[PDB]
Amino acid sequence: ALYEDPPDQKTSPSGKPATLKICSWNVDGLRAWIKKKGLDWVKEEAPDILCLQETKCSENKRPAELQELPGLSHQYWSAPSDKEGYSGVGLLSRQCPLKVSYGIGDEEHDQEGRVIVAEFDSFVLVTAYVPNAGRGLVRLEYRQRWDEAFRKFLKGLASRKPLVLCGDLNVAHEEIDLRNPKGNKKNAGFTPQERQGFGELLQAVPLADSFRHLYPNTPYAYTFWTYMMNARSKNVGWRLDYFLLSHSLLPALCDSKIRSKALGSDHCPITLYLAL
DNA sequence: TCGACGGATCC
DNA sequence: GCTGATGCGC
DNA sequence: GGATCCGTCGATCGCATCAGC
Ligand SMILES: [Ca+2]
Ligand code: NA
């Protein structure tokens, strides 16, 4: 059945108003999506920090609109080493960070342009586009390697500041995170492996699935639909885009939103509200 | 994802 | 620029 | 032996690149 995201709760569990509005979007071609009036949708949602994945854009092919984006002056970008047009993530924010880094500190995993780290006063923000195990599970073995190393990079970070991790994590965590769980229990993003890696990341770092913390039993809540087979219209999809945060931050959690209506990609955008 | 495909097996 | 083709994504 | 069950297994869509001239 269809899904309707409830209104934005902009109040913390202790009655404080939200201060920070992070918005993440797997854009699936930075150039297509801009052409598709995506940056329009950004201008109206008005985030403080905007994280994007699947940029598929070279450092010199980025449209000019982006730099001119108001309210998001500090703009950091990572694209892969030698695979032109693959992968790519960005992070834009109204305020300027204290330190920004790229990658997770592992040569094997920092070559496809997938991780940006943005340290602020009161927390650290990590945005990432995770490797898909692949059609035919061709890269599932490597995705076990990435999950393990990403796990311990975040455990590290977490020990020093409150962490917020967002973006496309390329796994549906539980049968409630996708419309066709039985049809997909051995395809990319729903294998016993990928799902055990998500749960291990949650127990080890540790982190909470922000959206599920609030709506732990609401189904058909998705962030991705295959372009094929007019699937978005039928609401057959996968929740692949998360905000994961340290338990420390749960008193600051006001709301975790899924922007189902916003068009421009095969992912829809997601939006986090914090009282900081 | 979706159907067309099997091949199993059920009355 | 314009045509073919192939790669990668759930 | 007819009609169901239930596991494969190609191909829709879209956004990129690359070869060639
Ligand atoms: Ca391929
Ligand atoms: Na009978």
Image (tube, coloured by chain):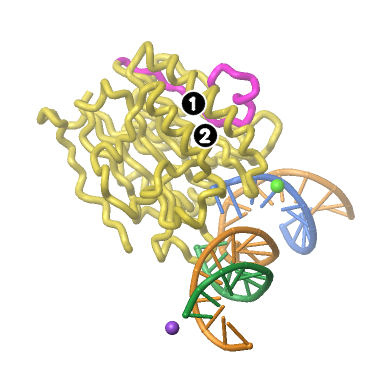
Chain colours: A yellow, B green, C blue, D orange
Would residue A22 be found to the left or right of residue D9 on screen?
Answer: left
Please give the range of residues in magenta: A104-121
Q: Mark 2 — residue? A: A89
Q: Quadrant of the N terminus of chain A?
A: bottom left
For numbered disc 2, what is the local secondary structure?
strand
Q: Residue at x 53, y 29 (%)?
A: A147
Total labels: the figure holds 2
The subunit carrying tag 2 is A
Q: Position of residue A40 (x, y in %)?
A: 38, 49
The subunit carrying tag 1 is A
Magenta span: predominant SS is: loop
Image quadrant, ligand 2: bottom left
Q: Residue at x 35, y 14 (%)?
A: A161
Q: Is residue A129 above or below residue A172?
A: above
Pointer 1 local density, CA inside 10 Å: few below 14, some 14–19, many at least 20? many
For numbered disc 1, what is the local secondary structure?
strand
Q: Residue at x 23, y 31 (%)?
A: A253
Nearer to the camera, A193 or D6: D6
Q: Position of residue A81 (x, y in %)?
A: 67, 29
Q: Is residue A154 above or below residue A56?
A: above
Q: Which label number is shown at residue A116? A: 1
Q: Amino acid at mark 1?
A: Ile
Query: In the current view of this chain or complex, which residue is farthest to the top?
Result: A160
Name the quadrant containing residue A46: top left
CB atoms of marks 2 and 1 within 8 Å: yes
Would residue A7 be found to the left or right of residue A153 on screen?
Answer: left
Q: Which label number is shown at residue A218? A: none
